[PDB]
Amino acid sequence: EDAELLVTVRGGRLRGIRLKTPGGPVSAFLGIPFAEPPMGPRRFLPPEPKQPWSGVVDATTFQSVCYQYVDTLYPGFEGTEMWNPNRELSEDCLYLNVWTPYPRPTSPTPVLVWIYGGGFYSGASSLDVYDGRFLVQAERTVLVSMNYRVGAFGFLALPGSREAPGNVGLLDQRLALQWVQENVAAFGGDPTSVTLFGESAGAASVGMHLLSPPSRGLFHRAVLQSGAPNGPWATVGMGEARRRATQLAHLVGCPPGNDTELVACLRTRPAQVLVNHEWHVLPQESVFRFSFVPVVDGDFLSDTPEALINAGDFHGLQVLVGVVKDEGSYFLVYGAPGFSKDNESLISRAEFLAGVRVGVPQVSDLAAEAVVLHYTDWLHPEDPARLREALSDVVGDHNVVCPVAQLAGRLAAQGARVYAYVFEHRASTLSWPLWMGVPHGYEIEFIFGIPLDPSRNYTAEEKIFAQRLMRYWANFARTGDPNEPAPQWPPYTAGAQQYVSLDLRPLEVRRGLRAQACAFWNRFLPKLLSA
Amino acid sequence: REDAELLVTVRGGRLRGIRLKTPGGPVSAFLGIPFAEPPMGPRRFLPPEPKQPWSGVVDATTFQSVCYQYVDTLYPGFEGTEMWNPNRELSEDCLYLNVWTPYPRPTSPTPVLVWIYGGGFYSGASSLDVYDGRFLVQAERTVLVSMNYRVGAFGFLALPGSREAPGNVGLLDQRLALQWVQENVAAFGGDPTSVTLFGESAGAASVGMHLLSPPSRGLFHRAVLQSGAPNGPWATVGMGEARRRATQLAHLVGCPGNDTELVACLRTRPAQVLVNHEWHVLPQESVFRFSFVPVVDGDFLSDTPEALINAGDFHGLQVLVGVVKDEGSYFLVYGAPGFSKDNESLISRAEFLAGVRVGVPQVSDLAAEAVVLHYTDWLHPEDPARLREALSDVVGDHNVVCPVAQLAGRLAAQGARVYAYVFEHRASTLSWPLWMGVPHGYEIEFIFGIPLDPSRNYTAEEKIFAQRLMRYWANFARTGDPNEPAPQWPPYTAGAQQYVSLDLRPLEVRRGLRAQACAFWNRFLPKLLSA
Ligand SMILES: *[C@@H]1O[C@H](CO[C@@H]2O[C@@H](C)[C@@H](O)[C@@H](O)[C@@H]2O)[C@@H](O[C@@H]2O[C@H](CO)[C@@H](O)[C@H](O)[C@H]2NC(C)=O)[C@H](O)[C@H]1NC(C)=O
């Protein structure tokens, strides 16, 4: 019997599994229950702590994926399937996973906590590309990842109601963070050194924990990859959340008014029925918009993330933030006219103008005209390749780059130490077409050291690159500074705006996260919308 | 006795001119030909009356008086400003024109160039040394005409709808002079079926207004617009604002209700008293705005120049347009905070933001914020040299470059053959400081061949350059094409947007009259001002 794989946590005993890596073994504890199953009458409600159990929980395999929409845009295509659920769907999904070195550390080891993305409508801690074994072996951290409710189950909100308060998927994350505080030392992890990191909606979640005081005491640093809580997609107002929740009820045959009866009827529906109507509550056809996201109702978030990012004192915070080179390209094939992964997507000017309304939904004609002004090359107004690149820039700037740049500049100007990057390496194995460049999400496999898997086809240079990135991230987790005793990564400041490029070449320091474009999204466009 | 070449009979009667010496040979000049009854006393503010015939011989042997006008005192005794100030006595008795012709007079009908001076509709005179027609006539063997027209209140005070002060009478002075050319120029050897108007700044705006006014349009065949356009935001005024300014002027000088009585009171005021109060009627502190300018009242202009340009059919028309390299710089020392000819004018960010409101007067705060967004380099938001250059661009783009580009693009798209230039040579004799670059107005001396004056010190290279520009201009007047019957000058079109640089080097073809900036001024900002 291997005592290294036996752990007692507060709720009882666990049995883990020893895994192989090219660098040697790691200990894994997969599918640890951290909440009571949010089933039946507990659907839409805040999570409750898992009650203690007798016997030994088998923690040798991933647990179920929280109920979510499954992408069918390109069936069987690797570029989309790698994000789809790779376990059975269930509402009984509140489990988390712990990877540690083997044998288990006997000195407090720094902890990384991963929060997956997926637009708050999808995602799972069990995805191959989030496999924690390489990071834990190479950099000797403890890695934790949790499942949290997505879609209606995590973020349907009738604000003011007790039956569907909203943001319970964020409380799922919070409960997992409290679980880490109480139990991670039993695995050799150090609860006084917890670094959150996440990508896209996971990065937005990280930012929301930064801005919510009950979460702030549960971790010490933050990494936001390709996402930010002030993204135009990351939160919804109370009025629009109520309208969406009420339209969902109508689409699945539930009354009307009274929130108690509405939620009671929703609780009688099979989970898949709610999933099947999720996208139809959005106000218009769009890309980069999701139906059920965090709601600003004064509780988890006392104000908009934007407002909270402006009012906060962030002295004592270190954050690592960044984007990929081509944030918008992946999102365009989900509704922008004329786009497809299977051709060059050389759109016409008419398609470009239509795409602006799809990629910047729910703004006035005047605001759309302002976008067209800034993103048109008026010496080549109709060039298809430039139009393709421009609309990719519109979607990536508006949704990712400029929200990240605003967060970075405000935090730095208000006392945080900020490191910024742009990830510029296109994986040799990438299945998406060349015109998409370095698409959203394709730095994750390098951060997690997936190239080290000998059963994959990465190059020798890409494995060295992966090791470099794992070292940056773990250096930051350990000290708040990614650098080592080699060209240096300088902090990002509101004035100098310095960031580094991450690719196969040594670090290159550059200035400005799309400064001209982001001045339009962050400084001028808000004035236009309110006047 | 008499030189037959210097005696000419026109409708009013007989004239006697002078034989002018030029470096290349003799020229005949008829200076100070009366073309209207003097607009004195009861005739102030009224449309021009045609000159009544006379017996005997009128000596047209020297320039007549400058129309009463403000005299610039910003830099007393400074060549760069004094060269534009009156060089003859001021008088309301000023409606005279000038004819230069080859000596001896042409045997066969000769193309006519008609010059309209600028000066913002508040100043200017056909007698300025820089408008000396003798070198053009001798070098290129055309007939050159220039006229004086009323400026300031005497030319453009308007109480719209009134009989006493209808407005635009300064434009009718120009028109009457063009009718005089049609009826009389053949007696000097000129060809009334080949008349090319050219003008600079307000003179270019005037040329464009004649293009857009049917009664003027039949009086000429081509047009040259140098650094000005009738759709400039300074070049016309609405009926209500013209009335407000005229009423304000009257109130400031003691007058008085019935437009008849108020104009009667204004007529009793000494001319200098009106001039002394002219700048006080502007609604705010500004640069590049002038109190009394053409009014859009449905008569001379049946609609705004913009609407007429957009609705016009311009087949059969050839036009030559252009700008100098630094249109804005000269205007900034007349009120932009921090600007001076006598220092480097390296302004702060605060002075830049203040300067935007001075250079873009009477727009909403949102409009001003849009200007700030477009002209700020957000990687160098506070760099003095960049801010100085940016404000120059603001004032130049808004008032000159973008109105000219809109005119050129719309005329080219609607059937006209357009040629475009940017003038990029800074004269070796220029007295303005180096930071002003190639300022507004400083192509004129080269177009008129002033470097060929023996008493001036231009370089030999500048004389060759002057000769080449005279050749372009006269080629265009003769044929509608500046090219020689050799780098070629391609027509300007709305798509390719080709223009040539004019400097000491051979012609260089470029694309875009500040296309990215002018898309903001010409396409987006009007939408913002509406909504
Ligand atoms: C550059 O000069 C401007 C203009 O000031 C005038 O010209 C100067 C060269 C100098 O001779 C001054 O005495 C003149 O008044 C300066 O802007 C002016 O600054 C003064 C005093 O600070 C102020 O009273 C005026 O209102 C300012 N005028 C304007 C148009 O803003 C400017 O400070 C000089 N820049 C420097 C010093 O580099």
Image (cartoon, coloured by chain):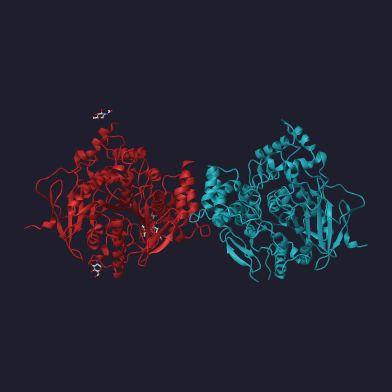
Chain colours: A cyan, B red
Q: Nearer the viewer, residue B345 or B30?
A: B30
Q: Is residue A86 left or right of residue A325?
A: right
Residue at the far bottom: name it.
Answer: A486
Q: Nearer the viewer, residue A463 or A103?
A: A463
Is residue B120 visible in this depiction of the protein? no
Task: Give percent across and percent down for residue A506.
Answer: 64, 69
Q: Residue at x 14, y 46 (%)?
A: B12
Is residue A329 visible in this depiction of the protein? yes
Q: Residue at x 54, y 43 (%)?
A: A365
Q: Is residue A190 left or right of residue B65?
A: right
Q: How many marks?
A: 0
Q: Is residue B346 above or below residue B183?
A: below
Task: Give percent across and percent down for residue B225.
Answer: 33, 53
Q: In which quadrant of the rendered view does residue A42 lie?
A: top right
Residue at the far left: name it.
Answer: B1
Task: Give percent across and percent down for residue A36.
Answer: 83, 45
Q: Is residue B372 left or right of residue A312?
A: left
Q: Nearer the viewer, residue A286 or B117?
A: A286
